Image: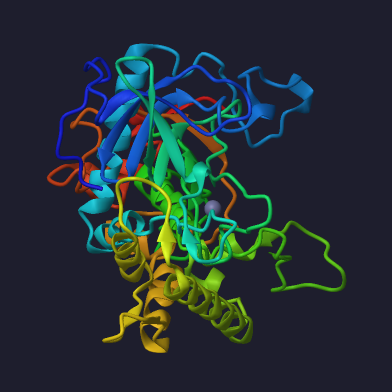
Length: 416
Ligand SMILES: [Zn+2]
C-alpha cells in the first residue's frame, strides 16, 4: 500500500527495508536487492529467473515458436536506471490503487492475509511454512528468515506474461484450502496493452474503432485481486474452465476462460457463473475456515522464537474474522464469513476498479489485447496518482483522450 518512504534503487542496504534477499528456490540463486515498500510487501526490480528453475534465462524461443500475444527483450530491466524507474513506477501504481476506497480496502486485506502456520506434522503445534518467507542477508553474510505476503517482481522471458504465482506444498493445496501462501506477482509498469473501444454515441461507426491503452493501475489491481484470493486460500482451481456459451453447440468449438479469471474480472463476465456453483464454493471454503478455527483451538505449542502462540492465534483470528468466546475458543460466524468472502470475490474485481478509477477499460475479459506499448508512468506530466493518463485540467481529461494511443501518441510507443 502507501509507501511512506522515498526509495531510490541506489540507496544503501540497511538490512531492514532495503537489502539483498534469497527466496525459497531449487537452484542456489545469487541474492537480489529488494525493497520493503510497506508491511508484508516487497518489490524486487529484477527479471524473474529465480522463482522457477525451468525459467532460469531470458532467452527468447525461436521466432516462429513464440505466440502472437507475447514480447521478448532480454535487455529489459538490466540497468540500475531501469530498476530505479521500475521501482518508482510500481510504487506510484500502489499509491493510485491506495487512493481509491476500494484499493485501500484490498491492500488492507492483503496485508492482513498472512499465510496460515500449517507447516507442522504435529496437529497440536503451529509452525510457519518455509516457502512463505524470504531470507534477508545480514552484514556477516548470515541470513534472517522473514515472513511476507506479497512480492512484486519483474517478468520472466515473456515480458507481458503477468501472473500471480506461489510455492506449493507436498500435500496441502495452499491457494485453495483457506491457508494461503506468499504471492509473487510478475509485473511491469513499463508496458501496457492496447484494446479497441467505440465511444461513438451515434450510429455511424463507418470509420472503425478507437485505439486505447489499458491503465497499468488496473492491470496491477487485477493481479492483486488474484493475490487476495490466494492469500486467503480461496482461489478456484485453474482446471475449472469455461468455454463461452452465448452461442455454443457441443463439446467446445472456441477459446476458453477459467472461472478464476472470470471471477476476478467481474461485471457481466462473472454473472455467467451459476449462482448454484457459487454457493457450492462458498460453503466449501466456509468449512475450510472452520477447520482452521479447529486447528487453532487444538494448538498447544508453537515453533519459533519471537511470537507466542496467543500472538499468532490473534493474527489468524483477525485474518479470518473468527469469533472468540470467553473460553478463548474460536468459531466461524456464517455472517462474517459471507461478508469477507463476498468482499474478496465479488467486491474486489477488475470491473469495480475501473469504476473507481473512472478510466476506459476492456468491457469483457474476452476482449483480447491488440498490441503492446512502451510507456513511462514516472514523470508527473505523463501520469498521476489521481488521474492516471487522463490529466485533469487538460484535453487528456476529455473522452479518455489520455488513454487514446492516437491522440496521446507521445505516451505510447508501439513495439508489436
Ligand atoms: Zn488474471
